[PDB]
Amino acid sequence: EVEKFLDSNVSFAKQYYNLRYRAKVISDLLGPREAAVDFSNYHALNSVEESEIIFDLLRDFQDNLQAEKCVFNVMKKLCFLLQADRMSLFMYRAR
Amino acid sequence: TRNILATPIMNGKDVVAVIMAVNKLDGPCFTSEDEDVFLKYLNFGTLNLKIYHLSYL
Amino acid sequence: ADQYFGRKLSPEDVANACEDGCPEGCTSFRELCQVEESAALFELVQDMQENVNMERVVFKILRRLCSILHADRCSLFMYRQRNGVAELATRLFSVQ
Amino acid sequence: IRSATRVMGGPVTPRKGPPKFKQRQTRQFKSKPPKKGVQGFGDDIPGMEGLGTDITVICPWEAFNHLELHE
Amino acid sequence: IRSATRVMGGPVTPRKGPPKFKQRQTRQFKSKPPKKGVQGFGDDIPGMEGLGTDITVICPWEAFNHLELHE
């Protein structure tokens, strides 16, 4: 048991892992859930594992894009990332 | 060919394409836990194929 | 060197400062396999910016989906109708 | 090489049989059957769905469907 | 009803002036100038965005594109 510690090299390791566990992680990240990031402290601007906002944004590209809820949802996070107070959207027409 | 796993791609009530995943390498056949990875990962290619079909019309 | 499956999965805990940990803030294998996938997904979204490329992006999706499932081949069939009857042509064959 | 399908002459096909051709389009209508459950891109165009008139004129009672049968 | 813009009853504008009305179009020329810029969705329609019918008639020598100088 403990003799199977040739794993001091990371070659066979992480290879067995992506062979036998990647599926569950990629199937739960893309499923219905909520992001896990604090949104009060304005902290560190961000970190690297902290960029699950990408997954949170991809989760809504599923069906029946209403084109109004999605823009609102991306703006409600771009407001936090930029550290701004207000945001707005103007549309273009010709008469 | 020995094992097969396939699904369609739908725009409303119409079909646009079909995708196949022939020939699994280790198990005797595809397990039941892959059938959800398949659907949850093709959700992004569905959008691109729907955009292509709409642009063509 | 051989694979003993057993049931021991505990060596997937928090890892100390080690090699091949280039990203800043990764403390587990799960974090690495999450960040890699997130980056791969942001790429191929950077490619639909203009002039939607039906052939190219689906090819890069299939190259990943063939690796995830441990399958050996993948394909793509298109649908069309001639004089009232339907049929399925071929557009991508033997992607590995 | 050989394009990965191993055919160079022209489109090949498994089946064989007698050809079948389409009939011409004789009569047209403004109406379609009522909508199904699920919808996709391009299925909301005015005038291309329904019977060409609002549902109120065909079913006047549906106008004030908010109030119940008490009155 | 806050309405998020503090305005109700009709749109408001910063400045007002005399009305200006569009003019008709008569000539309706076929051709278009050569195309520049990024493509974007909704282009490459065959019939439109082109001059005449084909490139060959416009530039008869262009057929010998792959050939070198000496010939």
Image: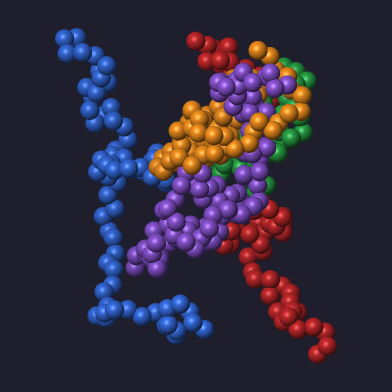
Chain colours: A purple, B green, C orange, D red, E blue
- Residue C20, given in percent of the width and then of the height, sits at 49, 28
The residue depicted at 45 percent of the width and 84 percent of the height is: E8
Residue E22 is drawn in which quadrant? bottom left
| Residue C82 in view (yes/no) | no
The picture places residue C50, in percent across and down from the top left corner, at 40, 42
Q: Quadrant of the C terminus of chain E?
A: top left
Q: Is residue E4 above or below residue D70?
A: above
Q: Is residue A89 visible?
A: yes
- In the image, residue D35 sits, relative to residue B55, either above or below, namely below
Instruction: State the residue in front, E57 or E16.
Output: E16
Q: Residue at x 48, y 79 (%)?
A: E3
Q: Judge left or right: residue B10 versus residue C61.
A: right
- A28 sits to left or right of C22: right
Asked if residue B43 is positioned above or below residue B28 in the image, the reply reads: below
Query: Furthest-bottom residue in view?
Result: D71
In-image side of A51 versus E48 (left or right): right
Residue extending furthest left? E70
Q: Which residue is at 66% across, 62% downward?
A: D50
Q: Residue furthest front?
A: A2
Q: Camera-side residue: D20 or C73? A: C73
Question: In terms of depth relative to the viewer, which is nearer, A25 or A94?
Answer: A25
Q: D19 or A43, which lies in front?
A: A43
Q: Position of residue A81 (x, y in %)?
A: 42, 57
- Number of numbered discs overlaid on the protein picture: 0
Q: In which quarter of the view is residue B28 placed?
A: top right
From the top left corner, tell me how far across and down residue B54 is, in percent: 53, 45
Residue, x 29% and y 64% (percent of image)?
Answer: E24
